[PDB]
Image (spheres, coloured by chain):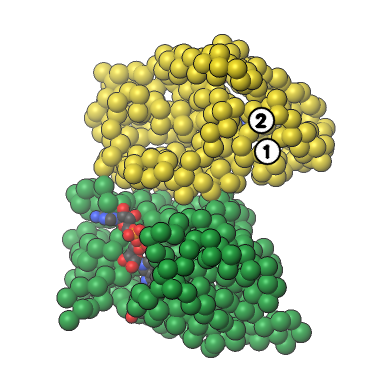
Chain colours: A green, B yellow
Amino acid sequence: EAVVISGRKLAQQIKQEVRQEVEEWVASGNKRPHLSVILVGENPASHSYVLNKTRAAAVVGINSETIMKPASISEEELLNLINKLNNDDNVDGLLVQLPLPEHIDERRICNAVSPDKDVDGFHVINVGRMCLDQYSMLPATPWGVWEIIKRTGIPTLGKNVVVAGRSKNVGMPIAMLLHTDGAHERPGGDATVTISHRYTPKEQLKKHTILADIVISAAGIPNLITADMIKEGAAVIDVGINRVHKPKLVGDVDFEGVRQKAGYITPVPGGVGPMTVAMLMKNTIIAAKKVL
Amino acid sequence: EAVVISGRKLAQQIKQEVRQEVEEWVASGNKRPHLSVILVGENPASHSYVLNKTRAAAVVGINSETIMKPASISEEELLNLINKLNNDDNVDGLLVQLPLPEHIDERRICNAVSPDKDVDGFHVINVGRMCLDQYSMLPATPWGVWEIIKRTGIPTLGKNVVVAGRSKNVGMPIAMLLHTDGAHERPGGDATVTISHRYTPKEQLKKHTILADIVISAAGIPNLITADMIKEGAAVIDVGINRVHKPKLVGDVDFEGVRQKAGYITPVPGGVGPMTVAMLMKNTIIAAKKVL
Ligand SMILES: NC(=O)c1ccc[n+]([C@@H]2O[C@H](COP(=O)([O-])OP(=O)(O)OC[C@H]3O[C@@H](n4cnc5c(N)ncnc54)[C@H](O)[C@@H]3O)[C@@H](O)[C@H]2O)c1
Ligand SMILES: NC(=O)c1ccc[n+]([C@@H]2O[C@H](COP(=O)([O-])OP(=O)(O)OC[C@H]3O[C@@H](n4cnc5c(N)ncnc54)[C@H](O)[C@@H]3O)[C@@H](O)[C@H]2O)c1
Ligand SMILES: Nc1nc(O)c2c(n1)NC[C@@H]1CN(c3ccc(C(=O)N[C@@H](CCC(=O)O)C(=O)O)cc3)C(=O)N21
Ligand SMILES: Nc1nc(O)c2c(n1)NC[C@@H]1CN(c3ccc(C(=O)N[C@@H](CCC(=O)O)C(=O)O)cc3)C(=O)N21
């Protein structure tokens, strides 16, 4: 029997910490932090995630606004709005919820957010700084993943990690953080990391996952990770979010099988999800204190 | 018997290509490209590598200057020089040979070179763009490594690659290029990539290298890769440079053992080295054409 790690309980801890930090920033005479979120269009999951973010902000004492725009907004208009928010000193953190309409170039939009306000860590400079193991705004999900590992007390240094997924927002940063030097300006995990993706044959995925002390799945494929792929005692972190069949939410991991073989496992929901939102809270206070 | 790939012969091909490109740029009325190299101090290997670079430039029709400064140069003075070269339009490519004296912060210096002239690809924006699979100035050694693989006709897509070394100038870019999507703006190799480093136990290094179709060693450890670590038919690319014992130059690979087990192997010297210099030539014409 795997220890089922509650990301909900961890996220509550992290939110207690942020509330304190925030209550102590404000207590000492500084402006309350303010997070602005641009939400374009009518995607329900997008609306639900933004709502989780604004509730979390309210519970740790961070002001938030949700700026709603229709999917018909031009790229030029959204960029204008971004420039206006970058230049407002009341605004500490700025994120644009993805995905955006097809007619809008997401890379351009992310690179328009000011790096000092880029609480998603998607701006190219934040990406470059992370890749160079310098202080940066880390993306929220990857940082959530590392915090689950670190706060549970699961070792990384010299350990074998497999990451299924190579996406610039999730997979790549997870791999980058976990493999890098603990002695650098931004310390990494010092793990031996294998990056797998859509062209990794299932056969080769299994031959690597079977050596792994930690397996992190961020592919968006149900049952991609099964018991026979895991060594006994492994930590299994499920970042996937998959709508399957009424519509239902599952992870990338066969939870019921793998919970009999792994030492640690995260559920979906209730695992990495809440951690994603908590770490965003942390980045907002960091942007407000202007410590980068 | 492994095919011993001559990086010398490949580099000559690449240099023939660059000469043509350059002869055709100039032929059409543009300024001859100009590469400036700042060399600080008296390190002999540094002097020898810069000399390889300026000879290569002369053979492909690129003007070069070597700017020599003493190890006593302040950081402020070197940065001044860099600003002056950034702002001169005769100068197309600008690199600072590393390493620098301890009193100088290399990250600051690399980030002062203008991205459009950063023919080493060390500037944070070039690093960020590479990490996001966008067009960037690629670092010369990593690109050399990928060119050896691609020009020999060794497949990467779906293949297992191990990289021994995680350095921001060599190991990390090699891993990044090889793992990434062939369908992105800057195409990657679509390989399954394992990053190993100084905290990977030898035991775990072997268990991954033994699955590898390609093993790329960039650790600076003699005999780090031996025959029993390699599967039969594997491609073995030796990026290491090690002074051993008169003083002698060897790679990270036990060449004599591994040439009996691998399908392909690169020697040291004569492998990745000349490729490092040729690809720098390629980046110089790219900076001159202002195509990024
Ligand atoms: N829980 C959270 O907080 C959270 C946050 C962000 C994203 N996600 C989820 O993580 C998953 C990935 O999100 P993303 O934005 O990185 O998505 P994406 O669709 O860009 O990435 C999918 C990645 O998985 C890889 N992949 C596809 N098939 C594979 C296979 N057979 N083996 C290994 N890798 C394979 C792809 O190569 C790609 O890199 C999704 O299910 C998404 O909903 C969860
Ligand atoms: N042929 C060329 O053109 C060329 C160009 C650049 C560098 N190099 C050579 O490549 C080697 C590395 O250069 P660098 O600048 O990346 O050096 P570096 O010293 O910064 O990097 C060494 C890397 O190897 C790793 N390492 C150390 N012990 C290890 C082990 N037992 N297993 C796996 N990895 C281990 C370290 O963690 C580190 O990431 C050196 O020998 C250098 O001279 C060659
Ligand atoms: N700019 C930007 N930043 C982000 O960090 C994200 C983004 N866009 N778009 C989509 C992803 C996904 N994501 C996210 C956030 C929260 C949760 C979450 O709270 N999950 C819960 C509820 C599951 C549900 O009912 O949908 C869970 O327990 O897993 C899931 C994804 C998120 O916020 N993402
Ligand atoms: N800024 C900057 N850019 C670089 O790309 C480098 C740098 N600094 N500092 C050191 C590394 C190493 N390096 C390099 C360049 C050429 C050769 C090379 O030509 N090697 C030959 C000769 C070996 C010898 O006799 O020393 C070989 O055949 O391997 C080796 C390393 C190089 O140029 N490097």
Q: Are marks 2 and 1 in contact (CB under 8 Å)?
A: yes
* Chain of the residue under the numbered disc 2 shown in the image: B
Q: Position of residue A101 (x, y in %)?
A: 39, 64
**Quarter of the image that includes the C terminus of chain A:** bottom right
Can see residue A221?
Answer: yes
| Residue under label 2 | B94
Residue placed most toward the observer, A60 or B226: A60
**Is A222 left, or right, of B73 in this rendering?**
left
Q: Residues within 10 Å of mark 2 (few under 14, many from 20)?
A: many
Within 10 Å of disc 1 (Cα), the crowding (few <14, some 14-19, many 20+) is: many
- Residue at the top extreme? B59
Q: Residue placed at 36% from the left, 28% from the top?
A: B149
Q: Please indicate whether residue B236 sits to the left or right of residue A226 in the image.
A: right
Of residues B208 and A196, the one nearer the viewer is: A196
Which is nearer the eye, A264 or A205?
Answer: A205
**Number of the label disc, if any, that sits on residue B139:** none
Q: Determine if residue A7 is in view.
A: no
Q: Is residue A207 left or right of residue A72?
A: left
Q: Which residue is mark 1?
A: B113
Label 2 SS: strand
Residue B153 position within the rendered picture, expressed as x and y whole percent measured from the top left: 29, 26
